[PDB]
Amino acid sequence: ELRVGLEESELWLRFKELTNEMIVTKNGRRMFPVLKVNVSGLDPNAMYSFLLDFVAADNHRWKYVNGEWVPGGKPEPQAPSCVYIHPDSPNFGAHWMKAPVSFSKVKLTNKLNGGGQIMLNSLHKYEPRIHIVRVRMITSHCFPETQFIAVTAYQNEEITALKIKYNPFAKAFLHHHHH
Ligand SMILES: *[C@H](CC(=O)Nc1cc2c(Nc3ccc(F)c(Cl)c3)ncnc2cc1O[C@H]1CCOC1)CN(C)C
Ligand SMILES: [Zn+2]
């Protein structure tokens, strides 16, 4: 029985509860927390490739006013992002099931989608989606705890405090809306 579990799901929930945010830049930024999954139930001798893309969690824009996230805008549907190929692809099912599969090197951008860079629209809520392709029978896997709003700068200052607390790299690289 094919099973895909989320690694460090409780840490993801700390950001999930406050509505997670991820920075997008012209050159791209790594995610925090990193997406890692545990896979069981593959054919260990078959060949598989692991793919990652980001789907719209909803079809409207978002704003952060008065210390809370508010929907808005005429809902225009957003197409999924480009796919990022896990660098170990293709590989045996035994390779994917021996250790957590990590997508730590993916970089989210708002400009250039080539290679390890994924282009996202600012102020939209995205959800990572993992594709396992037998080397084409495809299975797709997502986790609501990993949803986030792509932003060019951190809106919720509580998120900034969480990122600084748990991401060791946040400290090395370390206006409000009202009406
Ligand atoms: C983004 C580039 C991109 O993703 N290109 C691309 C994707 C692709 C896929 N994608 C895919 C989508 C959903 C899904 F569930 C799975 Cl398992 C896979 N699958 C197969 N081959 C692909 C090729 C590909 O590209 C190469 C082919 C054409 O150019 C290079 C572009 N955005 C506009 C979406
Ligand atoms: Zn989902």
Image (tube, rainbow, N blue to C red):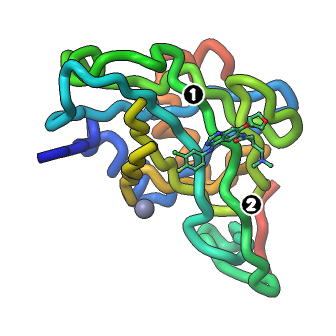
Q: Which residue is mark 1?
A: 85
Q: Position of residue 65 (x, y in %)?
A: 71, 72
Q: Is residue 20 left or right of residue 76?
A: left
Tell me which corner region of the image, top left, top right, bottom left or bottom right, holds residue 179. bottom right
**Where is ligand 1, by quadrant?**
top right
Q: Position of residue 71 (x, y in %)?
A: 67, 79
Q: Position of residue 125 (x, y in %)?
A: 62, 62
Q: Is residue 18 left or right of residue 12?
A: right
Examine the rendered structure and indicate whether residue 77 appears above or below residue 36.
Answer: below
Mark 2 or mark 1, whichever is nearer to me: 1
- For marks 2 and 1 on the same chain, the one whose residue lies earlier in the sequence: 1
Tell me which corner region of the image, top left, top right, bottom left or bottom right, holds residue 119. top right
Q: Which residue is mark 2?
A: 123
Between 40 and 45, the residue placed more toward the observer is 45
Q: Position of residue 58 (x, y in %)?
A: 60, 73
Q: Please report the residue visible at 87 percent of the width from the left and 31 percent of the height from the top.
A: 26
Residue kind at label 2, given as amino acid type: Leu
Q: Is mark 2 within 8 Å of ligand 1?
A: no
The residue furthest front is 136
Q: Please report the residue visible at 80 percent of the width from the left and 28 percent of the height from the top.
A: 114
